[PDB]
């Protein structure tokens, strides 16, 4: 249930680009 | 050998680019000029050329080093101005370099000693945060990574969720990166916007050896709760991590 930052596994692309 | 010597020629700035550098040097100290419509045109030349040279995956370290040197010889202010330009995603050359695992170029930028390594891109992340997730294969690279950690604030929190670089590394199970962050002063007790610590991230994802490494940190507080009152121990149980949970109980109570 990925509704908390600590449960997610963020992406390299998410770190470089948003909108 | 010598008869077979292949000289790499110096890279040189284009006429238009050298012109823009000289223009910038004369108006670097006039904020009115810097804000003008006409001067945006020269700033556009600067940003377009510099990002093309520094920030592609295929970037040539010798070319970037030649450019740094040429900017420096125009003016140290011009060098520091250009090195820290951000594009329309808020990314500097240091963000792209790190992202691409272009660590020779990362090393060049840090060595100019004019880089602002704490700059947040539009996504809200610092180069150190990107580094936490960047591929690293030779030990020569992890040394650049540790230089980058040393040169800036490893305890910055991202605009989304207030996550820390230590939390990102933990969540990917990157033990090498956790060790380097710890060695460069990452505080294990920082909480993100929801109250989560790196210890909680490690319990959520089941990284037993990371949990040991965090708990081995001198001031590590396993009693912190997230916003909902969850603890690392309770999270480990909820997520089905019985052995992390025993480790945590034992450290709270031995």
Image (cartoon, helix red, strand yellow):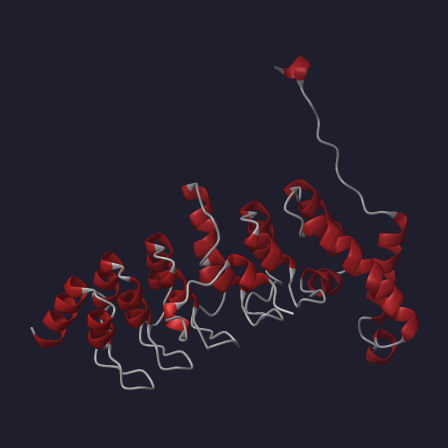
Give the left or right position of residue B89, taking residue B17 as reference: left
Residue lying at 65% horizontally and 70% vertically, measured from the top left:
A19
User: Can you say whether B167 is above or below B136 in the image?
Assistant: below
Quadrant of the snapshot with the N terminus of chain B: top right
Q: How far across and how far down the image is residue B46, in percent? A: 80, 59
Q: Nearer the viewer, residue B100 or B42?
A: B100
Q: Residue lying farthest left?
A: B254
Q: Residue lying farthest right?
A: B38
Q: How far across and how far down the image is residue B207, in percent? A: 27, 59
Quadrant of the snapshot with the C terminus of chain B: bottom left
Give the left or right position of residue B103, taking residue B228 as reference: right
Residue lying at 33% horizontally and 75% vertically, measured from the top left:
B197
Q: Quadrant of residue B76?
A: bottom right
User: Can you say whether B139 is above or below B124 in the image?
Assistant: above
Give the left or right position of residue B21, taking residue B161 as reference: right
User: Can you say whether B238 is above or below B63 in the image?
Assistant: below
Residue lying at 46% horizontally and 56% vertically, measured from the top left:
B133
Q: Quadrant of residue B6?
A: top right
Residue B29 visible, this orientation: yes
Q: How far across and how far down the image is residue B164, in percent? A: 43, 71
């Amino acid at each position: 249930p990925k509704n908390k930052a600590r449960r997610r596994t963020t992406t390299q692309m998410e770190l470089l680009y948003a909108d | 050998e010598p008869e077979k010597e292949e000289i790499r020629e110096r890279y040189e700035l284009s006429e238009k680019m050298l012109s823009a550098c000289n223009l910038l040097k004369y108006n670097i100290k006039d904020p009115k000029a810097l804000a003008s419509k006409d001067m945006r045109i020269c700033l556009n030349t600067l940003q377009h050329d510099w990002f093309r040279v520094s920030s592609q995956k295929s970037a040539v370290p010798a070319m970037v080093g030649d450019y740094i040197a040429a900017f420096e010889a125009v003016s140290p202010d011009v060098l520091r101005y250009i090195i820290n330009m951000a594009d329309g995603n808020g990314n500097t050359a240091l963000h792209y370099s790190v992202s691409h695992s272009n660590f020779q170029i990362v090393k060049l930028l840090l060595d100019a000693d004019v880089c602002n390594v704490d700059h947040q891109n539009k996504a809200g992340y610092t180069p150190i945060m990107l580094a936490a997730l960047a591929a690293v294969e030779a030990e020569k690279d992890m040394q650049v990574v540790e230089e980058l950690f040393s040169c800036g604030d490893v305890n910055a929190k991202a605009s989304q969720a207030g996550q820390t670089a230590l939390m990102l590394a933990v969540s990917h199970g990157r033990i090498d990166m956790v060790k380097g962050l710890l060695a460069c002063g990452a505080d294990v007790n920082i909480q993100d916007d929801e109250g989560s610590t790196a210890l909680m991230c490690a319990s959520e994802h089941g990284h037993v050896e990371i949990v040991k490494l965090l708990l081995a940190q001198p001031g590590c507080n396993g009693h912190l709760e997230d916003n909902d009152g969850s603890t690392a121990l309770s999270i480990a149980l909820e997520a089905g991590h019985k052995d992390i949970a025993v480790l945590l109980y034992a450290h709270l109570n031995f």
